[PDB]
Image (cartoon, rainbow, N blue to C red; front, side):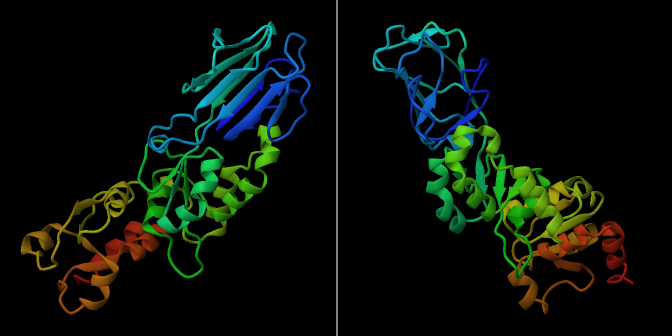
Length: 319
């Protein structure tokens, strides 16, 4: 998101978030969702046009900013951006840092890009929110990205948190839900006038951990809590692989379940199964080895006992 700020009284001492759209900047306009007042003497009645475009396809993956367009409105004294004269048919900027000077006025309008990219847990929630967030200048997606700052979990009364959510939690990502997204959309226009009115994602996130029995005390407790243990794992999602590695697990990945040699048993402490293979193939899985789902493993992880809990369960199924 583009934030603008000024080092005089010229923006009233308020930061503004500039969502995708078009803003008339000058001294005779008021404060709309589409008008910005700037008091100074050397600036025209209607001085500048700021136009913020919606995110590019790459912005989710690069973290780069929405295009910021600056048009001078046939001004006597002109407009400058980064000390270079804007004129002609305007200019468009892709840098994260913009110094905008209007006329001979020494107090400058400073645009800066604050990172916010939102990953979703599934296609269903994405479809529900994509276009909306696109209009708020927030890149969205399903794939992993080094630019992601926030992850949206599916909130559901019945079941476990998903693997996606377990992983985002352990990766140290801020987790948010549907209701934060509702909040952000109702206060859109108010936040343009005052950046500090921006809904706080950390409050939503801290509230989720507190109100939920499906989250450990801290991501830091879990990381490397199972180092020293090794497990075998039938195929599974790539989220599942990386999740287990963060827990400090040595991972062997078999395919058939009939790929279980004496080799594996002798060097594997327990085994992680898909939901499907766990329920029906209780007739054909190995006799000595402890078997659990990712869902159950996570429930072990939440406990204070984790290692003592798995240890004594290997000793139960070995005698």
